């Protein structure tokens, strides 16, 4: 629960020299692979030298070359830090995190801000405990910590306080006392032991100032601002918080459930998993914080029957399939529906394919699900199979996805008693999280209009607290922004 071992702005050479001059045998760090965008590299020191292990994320999961697949870098690191003797060349041990000092991935670091801007933002958007750290324009190389204190203006009950931070010999201080190795160490220190002014005011550092909430109508401008690197800084800052979602996943780790996971390490949270009324399926309920989703994996051969038990149990009437049955040569989902016009039984569940409708970007399958033994349990389940998603990367234009979800939305709305919408791909976190986050953001705009606030990272973080790894890559993070922008332009044209 730390994640100081990730260095977002480090070359392969610098990582080698940091392990050799400030590390020891066992010291490790992770960095984004500059060789290919979207990849990563685990750099470990061993026997007086540096070994680089490749981690690939094409959009579905983190693939540790020579290792196992994970939903987050945090789980990857924790897995091998606790299972000493799994990563091998001769076992290669992860012992000591080489902590990063870069604050460019901290939610509260706004190097650009000035004095007035910091006060204006903290005044207009901030509440009690809202703080931020910026670089001082007065003293080149120093920083300033701004904090708003008071009660939730124009009365004096609240105020803003500026606390200078001096950077001397690679370490930071507030003018006296202890000196910290980085701004993060300084901040985390005063989040526990807040400063106390001479007259009693406690400079509490509750939450960082929110700068990612925007008005939907003004999405076009925020997109341009994030393009000359902004997306990357904002996305890795979201990744920096993944270590705050280390929730219980005991049920998926039982022996009797191990073979129900397409990837043993990608598991559902206990507190949001779908419990079947034998009870286990790798799926989670996603509740936006009326319409909910079930984010789940692609069916294994031995989980098709459980999959339909879930669909029936939850009264789901729509399935969003976002992957071909095979991609890049490897399987991603077992065909769990019968051929057109055919009827087939999956355990106690019975499925008829009434008719298939081919579209440009997807295939629709009108399915009639029922329970064997009782001829009053029949309901129509509409499977929307999106088939035009590239094996590598993301769509170049979001119109296909948006038209796809627009149709999926209206079907769901036309069924009164409908339960959660089932969305799945390979591991059910990458594309599945992308489709679900876009659907959530689009829902808000369609209801409240373009004059509403939306917050992309906050929405992804809220979804990640219900299933780990939702939305996997920066390409998918950027594509979400583009889909929202495209949808906004449609509304403004009509
Ligand atoms: C410029 C900067 N150094 C990087 C971008 N920026 C921010 C701010 N806030 C979030 C955020 C918002 C809601 C939930 C979560 Cl979990 C997060 Cl992390 C974020 N992802 N980036 C500010 C500082």
Image (cartoon, rainbow, N blue to C red):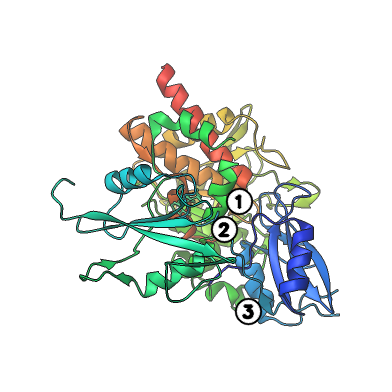
- 228 above or below 297? above
Find the distance from the CA under tag 3 to the CA under tag 1.
26 Å
* Location of the C terminus (image quadrant): top left
Q: Using the rendered view, name the quadrant where residue 398 is placed.
A: top right
Where is residue 225? Give x, y as percent: 51, 34
Q: How many marks?
A: 3
Badge 2 vs badge 1, beta-carbon distance below 8 Å: yes
What residue is pinned by disc 2?
469
- 39 above or below 398? below
Q: Is mark 1 on a helix, strand or loop?
A: loop
Disc assigned to residue 255: 3
Report the residue at 57% width, 53% height from top: 236
Drawn side of residue 209 relative to residue 422, left or right: left
Q: What element carries label 2?
A: loop
Is residue 79 visible in the rendered structure shown here? yes
Pointer 2 or 1: first along the chain:
1
Q: Using the rendered view, name the quadrant where residue 192 is placed.
A: bottom left
Task: Decide if ligand 1 comes within 8 Å of the CB at mark 1.
Answer: no
- 195 above or below 38? below
Where is residue 351? Give x, y as percent: 56, 48
Task: Decide if ligand 1 comes within 8 Å of the CB at mark 3.
Answer: no
Q: Is mark 3 on a helix, strand or loop?
A: helix
Is residue 406 visible in the rendered structure shown here? no
Drawn side of residue 205 relative to residue 488, left or right: left
Badge 3 vs badge 1, beta-carbon distance below 8 Å: no
Where is residue 490? Give x, y as percent: 46, 22
What residue is pinned by disc 1?
430
Residue lying furthest top: 494
């Amino acid at each position: 629960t730390s994640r100081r071992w990730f260095h977002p702005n480090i070359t392969g050479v610098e990582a080698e020299n940091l392990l050799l001059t400030r590390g020891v045998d066992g010291s490790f760090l992770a960095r984004p692979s500059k060789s290919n965008p979207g990849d990563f590299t685990l750099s470990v020191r061993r026997n007086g030298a540096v070994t680089h292990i490749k981690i690939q994320n094409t959009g579905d999961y983190y693939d540790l070359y020579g290792g196992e697949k994970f939903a987050t870098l945090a789980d990857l690191v924790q897995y091998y830090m606790e299972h000493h003797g799994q990563l091998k060349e001769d076992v290669i041990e992860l012992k000591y995190p080489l902590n990063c000092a870069d604050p460019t991935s901290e939610r509260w670091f706004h190097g650009h801000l000035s004095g007035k801007e910091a006060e204006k933002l903290l005044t207009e958007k901030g509440k009690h405990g809202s703080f931020l750290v910026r670089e001082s324009q007065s003293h080149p190389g120093d920083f300033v910590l701004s904090v708003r204190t008071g009660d939730d203006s124009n009365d004096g009950k609240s105020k803003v306080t500026h606390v200078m931070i001096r950077c001397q010999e690679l370490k930071y201080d507030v003018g006296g006392g202890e000196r910290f190795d980085s701004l993060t160490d300084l901040v985390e220190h005063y989040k526990k032991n807040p400063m106390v002014e001479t007259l009693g005011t406690v400079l509490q550092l509750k939450q960082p100032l929110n700068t990612t909430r925007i008005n939907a109508a003004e999405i076009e401008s925020r997109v341009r601002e994030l393009s000359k690197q902004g997306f990357w800084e904002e996305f890795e800052t979201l990744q920096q918080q993944e270590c705050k979602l280390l929730y219980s996943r005991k049920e998926g780790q039982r022996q009797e459930n191990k073979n129900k996971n397409r990837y043993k390490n990608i598991l559902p949270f206990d507190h949001t998993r779908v419990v079947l009324h034998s009870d286990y399926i790798n799926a989670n309920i996603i509740m936006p914080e009326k319409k909910s989703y079930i984010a789940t994996q692609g069916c294994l051969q031995n989980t098709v029957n459980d999959f339909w038990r879930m669909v029936f149990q939850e009264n789901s009437r729509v399935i969003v399939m976002t992957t071909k049955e095979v991609e890049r040569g490897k399987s991603k989902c077992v065909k769990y529906w019968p051929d057109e016009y055919a009827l087939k039984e999956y355990g106690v569940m019975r499925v008829r394919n009434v008719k298939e409708s081919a579209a440009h970007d997807y295939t629709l399958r009108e399915l009639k699900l029922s329970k064997v033994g009782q001829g009053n349990t029949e309901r129509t389940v509409w499977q929307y199979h999106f088939r035009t998603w590239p094996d590598h990367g993301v769509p170049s234009d979001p119109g296909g996805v948006l038209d796809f979800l627009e149709e999926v939305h209206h079907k769901q709305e036309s069924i009164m008693d409908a339960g959660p919408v089932v969305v799945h791909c390979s591991a059910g976190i990458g594309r599945t999280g992308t489709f679900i986050v876009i659907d959530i953001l689009i829902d808000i705009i369609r209801e409240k209009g373009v004059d509403c606030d939306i917050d992309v990272p906050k929405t992804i973080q809220m979804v990640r607290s219900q299933r780990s790894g939702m939305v996997q890559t920066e390409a998918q993070y950027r594509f979400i922004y583009m889909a929202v922008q495209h949808y906004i332009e449609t509304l403004q044209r009509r």
